[PDB]
Length: 17
Image (cartoon, rainbow, N blue to C red; front, side):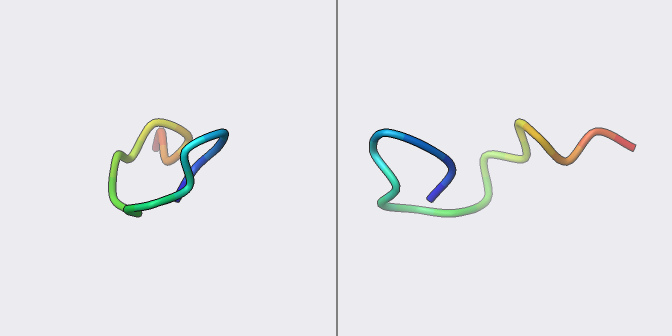
């Protein structure tokens, strides 16, 4: 559930390193 959609969790978009 990163941003505007916030309905999942796991995209790993802001999990760099």
